[PDB]
Amino acid sequence: ECHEKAGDPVSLVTGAEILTLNDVELPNGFVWSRTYRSSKASRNQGLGYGWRHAFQFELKEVTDEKHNVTSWEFISDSADEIEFEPVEHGSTSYQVYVGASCHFLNPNIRIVTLSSGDQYRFELVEDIWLLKQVRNGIFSTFQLRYSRNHRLIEVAHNKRPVLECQYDKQGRLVELLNAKTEQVLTTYIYDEQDDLVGATNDLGLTERYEYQDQHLIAKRVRPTGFTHYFEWSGEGSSAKCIRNFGDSGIYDYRFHYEGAKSSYSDSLDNEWTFIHDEQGHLLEKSSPTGRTWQWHYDHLGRKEKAVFPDNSTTQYQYNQQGQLISKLHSSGAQIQYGYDSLGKLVKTVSPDGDLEKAYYNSLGQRVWDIDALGCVTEYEYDKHGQVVKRESEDGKKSRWWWDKQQRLVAHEVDGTLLRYSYGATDLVNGIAYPDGCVAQISYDDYGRRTSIRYFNDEDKVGYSEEYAYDEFSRVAQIQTPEGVTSYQWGALAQQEAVIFPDGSHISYEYDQQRNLTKLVRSDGLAFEFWYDSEGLLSGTVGFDGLHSQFKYDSMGRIIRKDVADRTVLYSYDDAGFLQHIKAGNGKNIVENHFNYTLGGRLTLASNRHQTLQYQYSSFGHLTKRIQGQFEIGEEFNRVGQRVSQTLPDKTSFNFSYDTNGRLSEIRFSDDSLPKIEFQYDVMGRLSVTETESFRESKLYDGVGRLVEQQWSGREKKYIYNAQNRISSILDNTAGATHYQYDTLGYVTKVSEAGSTSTFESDSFGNPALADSKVMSDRIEAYAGVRYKYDQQGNQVKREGDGTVQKRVFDALSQLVEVHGDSSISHYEYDALGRRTKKITQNGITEFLWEGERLLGERTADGFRWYLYQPETYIPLAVLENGSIYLYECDQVGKPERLKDSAGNIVWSASYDVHGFASIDVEEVRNPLRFQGQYFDQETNLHYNLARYYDPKLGRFIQQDPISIAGGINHYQYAVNPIQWIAPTGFLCEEGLKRLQQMLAEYQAQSDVPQEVCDQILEAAKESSVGE
């Protein structure tokens, strides 16, 4: 038995049907669900026959005729029973092969700690044990109260009631109140028979249920529609449900029994086999493709060994207490857990040798937390049992404030101290930031968010955002200052269509089993998907072809891509990691080599051009980077911070942190270079950079947008339009630039001098100039330049004004050579996909990488290192020939000015709208154009991390391996290069991130849904492997 689309996973071979539905959900951790069970559907308590809410716990005490108890029965959801033996006071039961325990604190207090991590504190009143505490999480608890009659009412959230039960005089519940501005939420409906028939949700949704003859579910009708039918072949609790009819996306679900095995059909003619023993123990599970899972028990009720489809075994080892002690994998490492006398997880050992432990108080509070890297965290609770401090080592201590109503009044992380304010109900309507900004939220009468309005005093800045929902439960329209966006769902949360401004529409066509089949745009181009019998992506077709194969393994891992020209031939370590990659295109082999240890920490990535060996000392932190003939060390502190990074040039600059755990001082070891100091803002943003000869200060209007920059001799101001876009840039050194955009985010025209520039484009980023010529998505002619592509979709030939340039790549779609008129260049890449050596006519250039960003280079004239911001890719204070040169970057991070510590500027340049830089004063070269971009002059290109960007055309010259998961346009760099940085190539984002942007709700729409996006990301491992 297993999961099916027309219901819930089956819990018994006899055909026990389960149905879990959530009635109400609160956005603070509260939920009210219900569970139905076809088996044992002859008892009625609370709801109808078989229905049970999540707060029904009895803990009965079984008695016999001899006036002896000898048994305590604990009943949980889905009719699960556990038997505990009677013990004396101050002792526990230590139940076997279930992993539970029954602690007896006092004669009226019991604690039932299950294997999940709950406590279930029960209290005796006169003769029966009623549930009083749940403690389903670390901070989420549930308090229960009872009246003179034994009925559950007044459910609370750790201090305060948020729901009711409103029991009826008949003996059931019909309506659920709110205990605060009382209003109907569920209004259960009952017929003359004792069985749940109608739901009648608060928003008007009515879900009907009809039982055939014996309170067994025969049909169910959702409020939107797509009813589901049921048929049975037995009587009573021994009835086997067969032929589960579906109507939304499924149309066939057959179940066949044979007494010893069970076969399950599907709507795509796919059957799974299940073979059980004489009991409910699952022995074998067979897939229609050939994958077989096997289980072997220890003749005690618990599992002992598991066998996967591949030739591997996983064994378990318990103790005399019935808890899981160790789990060992075949030809690998093992995991070891350790519990306390109560039965909660207290210690866990990782396969890499890093232990994680904690401590639980006598009231369930967790204190003295220690992570894997090593950090003592001290928890502090108030009189009401809520964390107030959560203090770690070296700052990183939060602060929480509560009122008489025990509501979140103030929360602090690193010094923000933002305040919250609630309205007339238990919902926060106002947020006050320490910079003066105030964000108000306006809701509707159904408790949903409708409007958000930001406003700041003494500056007159702010905007608004609005949302409009659909008929039943979905979002229909979102109105932002940029524009309006509409959505159309397929009555099953599928979003059949999305509508973007300027008349843009994207349609999604699904198929059976609810799989994304086709994505159609407005111009007729379609992206097609094809799945196999296993539900995985078996093929993809882009807007211009590019067929794929996507071969998988017996465990669910991709083996080869084979996208119409070249396979990758992935080879795994046979333990859970990648080992080898061999790609080929026209007699071109790369032969990458990967080595991994038990639990990560590869420490090795071998290639034909590099070695890339790493070293770890202790606590799981890296301490040595050995790249080719270069060695970089580290001096990680006992608290986890890193200081005194040693370089092969014997520089070894030291770091010094301050309160709240932030970088505050950088002191070189040369004893001749001055130190650079940083000063952050109350909001947590870097504001001042101070040095004896360089003072930089960036200001903010009070909302989170950068407005003014000063460098003690030069000032830059930015003026935004009504659409929250950079409109005017005024530099103190005789400069005024104005931008004008279209209805979308693209730029239409720019004016910087007596001459102006104009651009035209459609709603998909393609150029719409008078001389632009594109076939489907690639540019064939632009500004008199002819581009000749290949079968893959990469710029191969470029014909400009009397100049022809050819480009040749490798089998990994990486540019390896470029031929021109008199300049032939070659490039070398390592196993991580980064450029390590450049061979040109000028000389040999070597690059050193530190993670994802570049760190220094060697141009055969000495050593020069590049420094960046603490947590930003903006370069600053480059070190060369024992001299520090300070940079001056704009709001995007493009270095335009560079000056030594003497008062005179040594490098000056100016950038255009397309990213090209015209240099006028050049004494010290600066090949950095954007954040993480390297500028090649011999080819006049930009290289972020794996792709070449063209500053003249304004977009990349090749498609990324996650093009479908990145955006609708495979060549678009960004919608506008004024507010987007897009580091490391793909995955563009905003350059400046504001804290107020976290309050806005999710857009609930993407270019590709999460499932297909994850399936695409997992299918491309050659570009996602790192450290």
Image: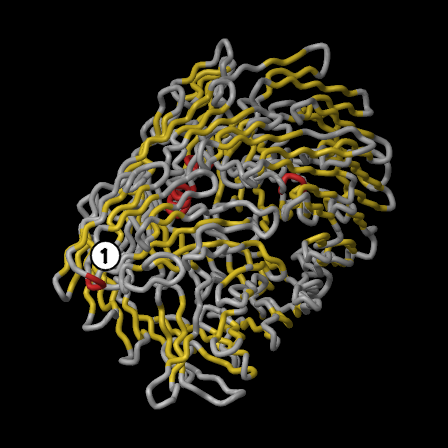
In the figure, is residue 580 to the left or right of 252? right
Nearer to the camera, 979 or 212: 212
Mark 1: few, some, or many residues within 10 Å (few <14, many ≥20)?
A: few
In the figure, is residue 435 to the left or right of 496? right
Does residue 328 sit above or below 457 in this rendering?
below
Secondary structure at numbered mark 1: loop
Question: In what quadrant of the picture does the N terminus appear?
Answer: bottom left
- For the view shown, which residue lies furthest in the left direction? 258
Q: Quadrant of residue 204?
A: top left
* Total labels drawn: 1
Visible in this render: residue 389? yes
Give the colour scheme of this rendering: secondary structure
The residue that disc 1 covers is 214
Q: Residue at coordinates 69% horizontally, 22% vertically from top-left?
A: 721
In the figure, is residue 268 to the left or right of 747? left
Percent of width and height locating residue 12: 26, 64
Percent of width and height locating residue 663: 74, 54
Visible in this render: residue 549? no
Does residue 739 sit above or below 389 in this rendering?
above
Q: Residue at coordinates 54% horizontally, 65% vertically from top-left?
A: 147
Does residue 795 sit above or below 561 in this rendering?
above
Does residue 339 sit above or below 182 in this rendering?
below
Nearer to the camera, 582 or 842: 582
Residue type, numbered disc 1: Gln
Q: Residue at coordinates 80% horizontally, 30% vertically from top-left?
A: 459
Nearer to the camera, 839 or 507: 507
Percent of width and height locating residue 284: 22, 65
Q: Quadrant of residue 811?
A: top left
In the figure, is residue 590 to the left or right of 373? left
Percent of width and height locating residue 62: 37, 80
Nearer to the camera, 85 or 1011: 85
